[PDB]
Every structure is written in C-alpha cells, then in structure tokens.
Image (cartoon, rainbow over all chains, first blue to last red):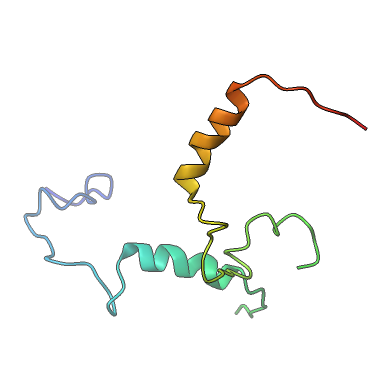
Length: 48
Length: 48
C-alpha cells in the first residue's frame, strides 16, 4: 500500500534513519559556504 | 569585478582581513557608548 509517490517521501512510515550526514569532514555550513565561494569565481561549462 | 555593486561586501570576492580592527584602543562594542555620550550633549556645527 505504498505505491504512491505523493506519500512516498517521508521515511517516518518506513522506520529507518542515518546516524550522521557529514561528508568528507564537511558539515552543512561547509557546503553552504563553498557554494558561494565557487560562485564568486566565474567560469563556463558544457552541456550534452 | 570592476562593477561597483559588490565591493560593499568584500568577503565573497577579496575576503581581506587586517591583523586587528582596533584603533587607539577602541573596541566595536565600546564605540557605541562614548558615541552616545558625545551625542547626548547639545552642539553647534559649521556647514560649508
């Protein structure tokens, strides 16, 4: 009875979780600041 | 970055920071109190 992508999102009904979320020794604020740190340096990319 | 609309906040582009922000032994929380004390008394000023 869980085939609905509308109700598929929250994991409370699924009973699982993670202990930590840090990546490469960087907390949420680290990404939240490196994003604008890289935005300050303008550049170009490609698209396929 | 010769456009003048980001030099207001330098932390993104240049993020410079001197050794200390002191001036004649004046601390930022300090300045408020003596500024208030000076402006408390009435004054006369010259405008050119």
